[PDB]
Image 1 (cartoon, rainbow, N blue to C red):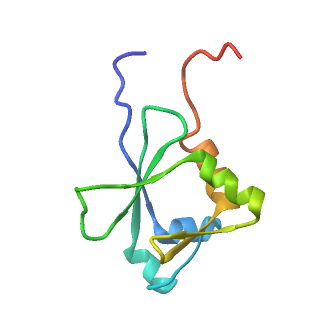
Image 2: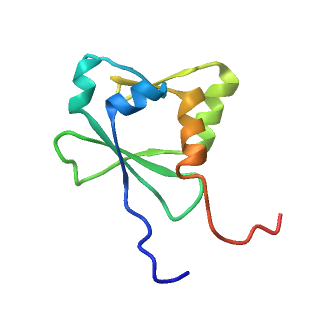
Image 3: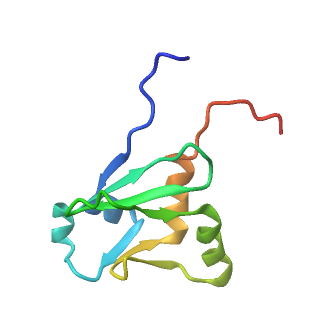
Length: 112
């Protein structure tokens, strides 16, 4: 319960997210190029906020954040496609689905 290596940022390739359906396309590279693209999603201590980083150059100055409410706001409006970094595109309908099982999974008391 205590002695357990927890944390670490999830590492997935662009092709992986594309194959599943999450990642739509990228306004810069091609489908076959996805193989040379990896996304590093760092988790958070709280529930709702997430760290979305794209391994390419190595920006250790800041990281793109992604709230949970924002993802839902798009579902209510209609925006199915999400413009990331004004280039990469991900499906909001599937993006939330994956995280719902990936990160979404605490191990504490609920009481409600």
